[PDB]
Image 1 (cartoon, rainbow, N blue to C red):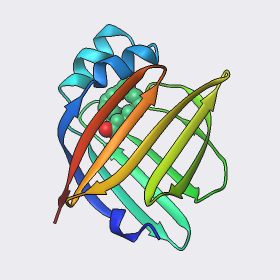
Image 2 (cartoon, helix red, strand yellow):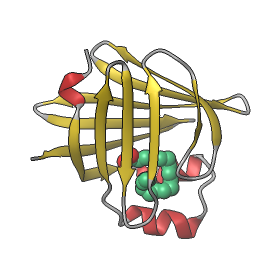
Image 3 (cartoon, helix red, strand yellow):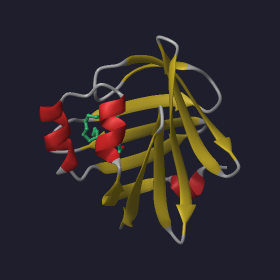
Length: 133
Ligand SMILES: CCCCCC/C=C/CCCCCCCCCC(=O)O
């Protein structure tokens, strides 16, 4: 049941995103621009196929996936990963695997805000998105 996540969301807070990017090996110039970027995330469904768009003035991505079915993904920072997205404890959990590394991108709804928690290595980044009408 992912319906409450659907819609258009805009970034309104970010904590520790530089640490997360640095942990992934993102270069300093990309981190600089990324630290000042406010993406718009659009989450749509057609049956159990979700499409998650992330749009910004810097990088854009789009993925489509069936919940619970692995898919290939090429991330905004150009990692080629094996991914799966599932609903777990009411949270939309996106796991990426590559070269034996793992990162999770976890989305949950708290007081009407979408909280995205990004974990890689020890780095834990929390980004907050609010719904656009
Ligand atoms: C498409 C926009 C990507 C996030 C902002 C620009 C950063 C680019 C390089 C680092 C990418 C790291 C993995 C993706 C993080 C997504 C964050 C988010 O959706 O808020």
